Image 1 (tube, protein in one colour):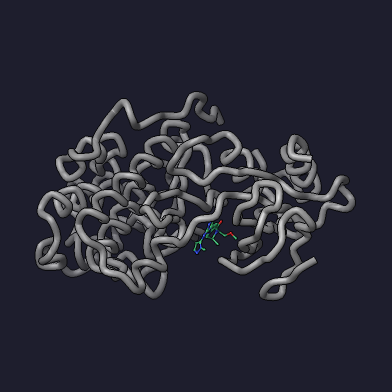
Image 2 (cartoon, rainbow, N blue to C red):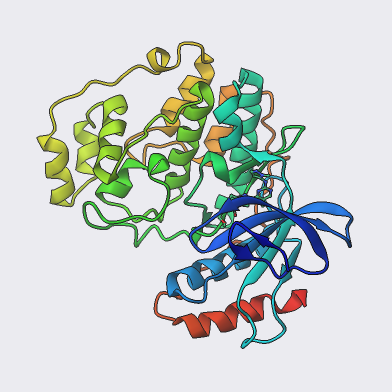
Length: 343
Ligand SMILES: COCCN1C(=O)c2cc(-c3nc(Nc4ccnn4C)ncc3C)[nH]c2C[C@@H]1C
């Protein structure tokens, strides 16, 4: 029973030689040697039972990832848990090991246009598939984008992922949000729950901008500051953009701000490709209805060397549609049942 960074992993004895990769609010990720397959693997310990919200996410993550099979999305190779509900303390997810993630790469390495183009291609290919299943990732960021020696890109961390619910998206001004701040679409701050596909497109734009400069484009130090970084670049939203925001608190806040002009993409990224900046402009659109969809982003002249509709698969069976009320105990039961097949 090895330990890492204060947590105990009950992966014995099939997986050994552990090391630590990442941490989460209710989960930890570590590398391990798998004897059966004779290769290095990623193991995700998830402790969601104490809290209810964590149980919902965990069930959603396991169900989504078991559903998916895509070259650009992390899969589940195995699920380790205790044989009984009473003995089930933690849930262990075995996934393929990736060399690193885009966050780590960006901290130390300059990316060439070729790498940028190809990374964006694989993100959009993976996202096209996620979206075709009627799934929103909701937490796209460089640390959720894994890479290997040959530059293959895989999307991971589906804990915050939900089935799309456009009808129930509207909400009040300054409504709290879980997902990473720097990659939040401006609507989240003003009138959205993050229940539409356009939410992920905005995150992809932020990543593209971070690939062009090795620095986050909108590094807001707090909830409101995030919005003011966005408007600082995008300029004051148009009359037509403001008209789509009907809740008055959000509208009156935008109207009270002094007029700021749109900073040009070329001035922010002078070394960037002109086609790359044209796509970035489309992704980073203040109005979510005017924002480019994943399939149009793939069809963009910046990705014409990789664009192939036939080689961009979509989900065979999309998710159709209530864990919000279900307590930690009933959720522990569904998690146990969803992980049964791996015993
Ligand atoms: C606790 O959960 C929080 C969310 N979260 C993940 O689920 C997860 C999974 C991986 C992961 N990471 C690598 N390798 C890699 C990334 C960075 N350095 N190295 C060696 N290989 C495979 C996987 C599946 N990375 C992450 C990022 C965070 C930690």
